[PDB]
Amino acid sequence: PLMLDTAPNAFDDQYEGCVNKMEEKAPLLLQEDFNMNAKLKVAWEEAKKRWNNIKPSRSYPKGFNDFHGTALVAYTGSIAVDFNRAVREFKENPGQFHYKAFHYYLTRALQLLSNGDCHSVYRGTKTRFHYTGAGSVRFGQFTSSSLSKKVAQSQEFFSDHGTLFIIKTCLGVYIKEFSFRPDQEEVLIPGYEVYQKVRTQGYNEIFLDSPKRKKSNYNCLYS
Ligand SMILES: NC(=O)c1cncc(Br)c1
Image 1 (tube, rainbow, N blue to C red):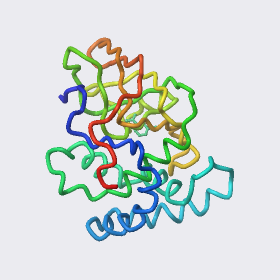
Image 2: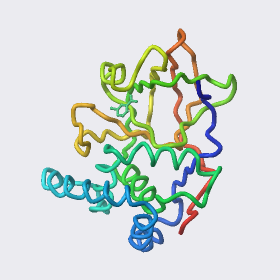
Image 3: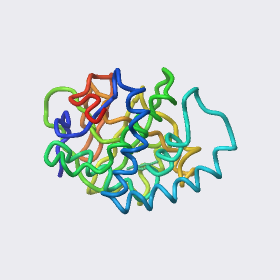
Image 4: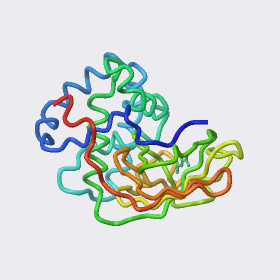
């Protein structure tokens, strides 16, 4: 069982005040991330091809480019596990975060696609989570959820040994049209969204509500 807390160790950069500076530096950093992360490089190359195929479909916000589209696609792929891990364990080993540009492009993609809408989403896990007992909570790492309770409860993500999160998010973004799995009806939640209302329901259900944006512990770290 894992604890549901404020994720004090997670890299949670919101890039406040350095968007343009990161835009300029991220291309070089992306290349550095690849040199330090061969798997990431493979995952990005795969995502780039998928993105080249899907983008002609619709339009995107002002400023949204191939880096943002490819990062989102790539997140719905195999690189997710390691990336979420690195983000989660950031404070414990800062010199091993080989996702400097990746994290930026993914964060910015979510920021660009976000409007003020809130969604009712669900997230299932194989690992049981326990609320610490006090204070608001945060996931820290980017967090996948679904509009479909059936998807979140599916054998793919959930089990009686884990937890089903029932969530009301207002920073989450519907990214179905980017995913390698459109069927999952995914809503991607930034790790910096805080839930001021936490209620445990039964042994495997946790209700998260009263979502709020909250200043991060890290800001423009690699700018
Ligand atoms: N853990 C989950 O419920 C989940 C994880 N990834 C995508 C989607 Br949709 C859901």
